Image (cartoon, rainbow, N blue to C red; front, side, top):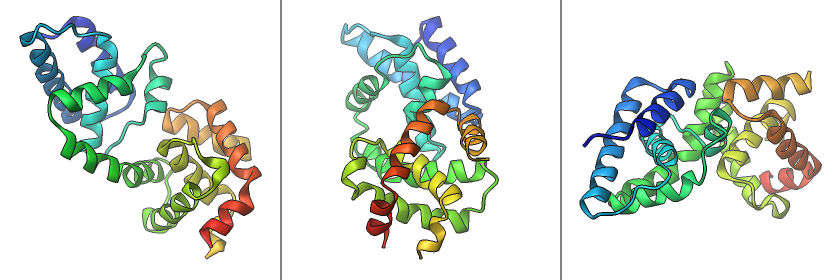
Length: 207
């Protein structure tokens, strides 16, 4: 199965900017060939090839427990569209429902670990704590609508800047995190301002 140049170029470019391991790209290529080969054999149009590429890469990255959240994908390539729809299409047509359910269950931990390692922080300290912060955040009404990735970002930055560990420059910290995570600093500011405003509610959920 020969993939369209735009499909390959997008995947290679995004994989490069994400600083992902080589065999993740190879897995991304394999998923795309199978999906594209499936569609071609049934006479189905392959729409939005760059988005299909991103989605294949994300499945691959999650399988290697090096998750690539959508917020990062949009920050690395601002032109990509409805990547989530394509991911659902791939999962369904390649029959990956059982694997996808496992990926969804481990996504939060694996992203936490990824960010903790990127920030030069100690996993054995931050992981079990930020995990508990994560659970707390989901029980806070004002924070409904935050994505899993938004909650991971919030839990880590709260643990790093809001002294939440005692429950058991600031712009420069958010900016450094944002660069290292390949996230939009303005989106991180917004999520944090929302979480910081409702700080005592997060604490009560935590305790």
